[PDB]
Amino acid sequence: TPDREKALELAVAQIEKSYGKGSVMRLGDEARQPISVIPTGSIALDVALGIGGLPRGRVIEIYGPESSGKTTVALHAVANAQAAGGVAAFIDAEHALDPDYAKKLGVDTDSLLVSQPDTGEQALEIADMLIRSGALDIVVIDSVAALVPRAELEGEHVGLQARLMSQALRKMTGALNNSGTTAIFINQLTGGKALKFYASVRMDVRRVETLKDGTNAVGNRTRVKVVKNKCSPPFKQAEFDILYGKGISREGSLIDMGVDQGLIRKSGAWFTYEGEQLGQGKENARNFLVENADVADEIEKKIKEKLGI
Image 1 (cartoon, rainbow, N blue to C red):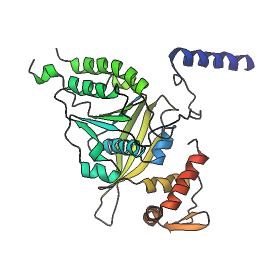
Image 2: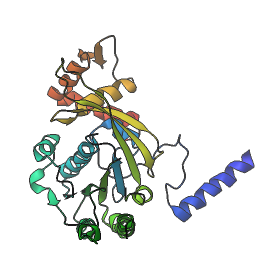
Image 3: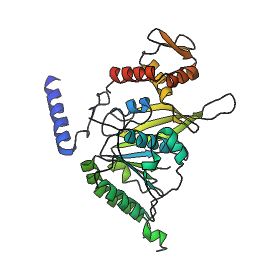
Image 4: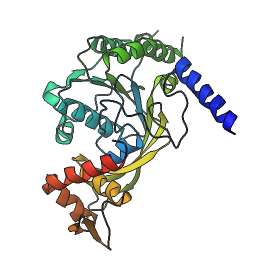
């Protein structure tokens, strides 16, 4: 029992030495807090990720169905990275991006670098050239499935989209570590059978139920599961709202995590905080914290403190 704990601690130690700092963890463990992370938009998701957001210098994969929220999540990462004086690229083989939307989340679309590559190979290469500059904080690739190989596009065997992904990632991982740039690969349901193993974080994004606005019904309760996480115990999940043309309700996630930690009391429909009242029902409580940014930062401050960061 006492002679065991050492052999295990020893075992865990040489594993970390041989393969890296997150190669083994107990699921109950507190997270190793890095210097800087890219916040995701939802404090719940930031907390579910352990390190308060996305890791820098690593490969992230965000996947899920059509219109599930993955891209929304990705754009927030882009917004936050910029808000911190960072530069961001967007490799687009999908041609789906709505910048007016991106802009409302907080993306500085004017300074957003975009590329609409001719081929899968070119997409990844252009992304690599960008990464090896050292000037990028984040780059998003929309999407994996769209990374069609030159050969296929030129009418010329089958299965080389995977070889392409595999080859690219090998190179890209080293370049991402050195630069400290984060790559977000958006993926559906591909060639990302490699992506699965190169990724430090993998997020399963899904729509749970549609938010009611008196019968109009615009907005979605989004659920994300961190199915892989090399930077903190994995398998944590989070919920948060994405609102029609507004993105993730930062304030909505503040309340939810707020009550979760007991920092926000909930006597009936009344959400309460530090003796004062925030609103009756979640909508007013949400609407309160947006028109009162002072208290929203207070609550955000208190939540980070009570947890890791």
